[PDB]
Figure 1 (cartoon, rainbow over the protein chains, first blue to last red):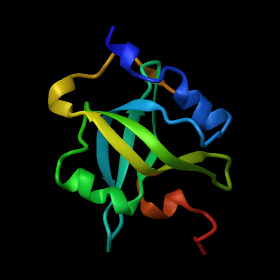
Figure 2 (figure 1 turned 180 degrees about the horizontal axis):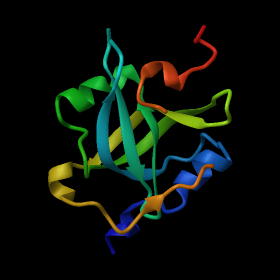
Figure 3 (figure 1 turned 30 degrees about the horizontal axis):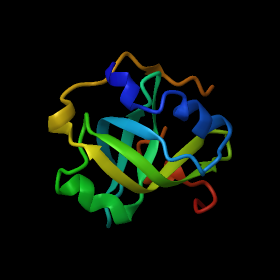
Figure 4 (figure 1 turned 90 degrees about the vertical axis):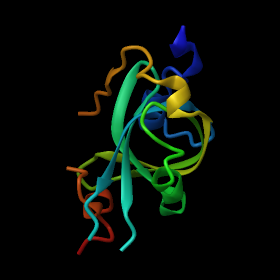
Length: 121
Length: 14
């Protein structure tokens, strides 16, 4: 199945274990600029095939991937470096520092599988 | 909310 291409379970692992050694393969579902007012910042809704999670921000060094439309919704990418930070109220956020587009949005064409929003509380 | 850049970082926020 198409979801055989994605690292099922990696979103829960990122948010619960925080081991930055995994190099999960994820699908970009949506990309939205974050209000900045300056360098633009991009928020990503990501999927591991089981869950979606919108608490991803691109490092600014990766902005050209979005702006030159090499990283776009439906593409499949491998995360090679990320960090997790925890906010005062307990919410966790993921900063994507290095990644590789494995399959372009045009080659994938659709959201893979039926992922459901991650339950973070 | 995570819709503004300040939301992503509390310790830089005064």
